[PDB]
Length: 246
Length: 243
Image 1 (tube, rainbow over the protein chains, first blue to last red):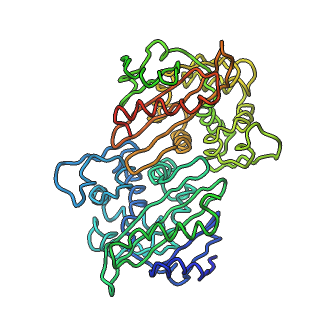
Image 2: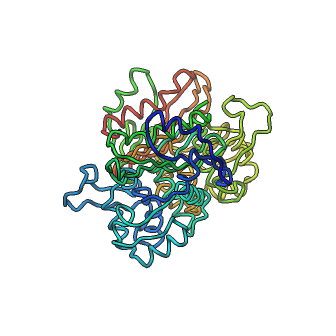
Image 3: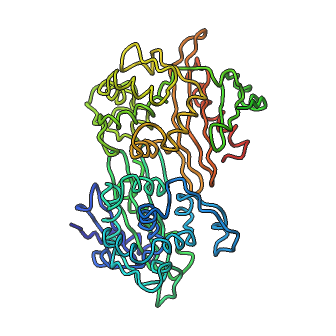
């Protein structure tokens, strides 16, 4: 079940942006959102697909284990930050596309199609090129579907070993305090134009004391400088609900 | 293991007697400020929550990573412990009473078996099942701490990989895209001037594609000296570029 709270639009409106935030306390049976219609609307996952891709890589044996090093060959990459050896965690956190494109090629379409069926991952459309379907292809997923998937991973309920789900979970840790732990992943398809905006994402979950909150945010992005709102808007909404600190 | 006596400069301003052990990549490449004290065995205090947590999970006393340890509402020694805690929570705030009840449910026979398996110090759990790591005869060295933590890091402990991974996420204390610290503090008490307590900070640091295993302990007879257990080792590691 999901409820609409359209007074969460004032963080979007104050920054002049079109987007959705979905927040669920304890499980996905208790979700709220600022926009019910946008919550179910399906968007290119962009680098939030590294979550499922890493699990699939581990399940198929393409990624050997938690300590595998993805070595840089010396050939130039898009980002200088990607030009280095990377652990699984490092590649996910710096969002190293070329590493996941190679994983995806090794997985192959047949196997990638199988696991996205098992994970109920959006429209499950990986057509058009096996190393770009999440970056510029036909794959689409909603904020609600992101929360469902992440809740599954949290509980170790995906069709994968518990070990592999735990390995990916530690790789998604982005904030840590004794009684506050955040697992998250950003995504960004690209700066679009005003009429054909790109999409930006922030998805994950927060464990605060003994409670858990699943979240998924997306927004239209048509200006490079508005990228940081993918975290600031969700933070302020979560802060207004009392989740951050006290 | 090699000796680096220039690291003694980090102990001298606060007049700390203690040892740091630091290993790059594996436990066959270690260095320390004091080779003598590196092998010397001390009460583990709350660093024993690492093995205790694994054993709790292995035996089924702890059901899984999402078990909540509800507070019964009865007085505890620290205010930070007076609340429901997750497994990670209880390790991170070092909630003794939670692990005391865990140790009772594991029991002496099972506790003995797992500490032999883990090669954990002198393996002496005498003096009461719920206080042996705090007040008892259990002793472990900094070198033995690094060897144990390396085994955990590689999933080589005799426990399920799942359970080892569960405890590892509970030890995360610092996180960045290419920098991850797993750690646990320990503090046995102030003892006396003549027979001081011991404080610990143990764990490992992942920077880029390298891993560093570390163990620090120090004599302590005043509670105001406590944060030196992390700042001395932090200063040493930062001076070697681990930061």
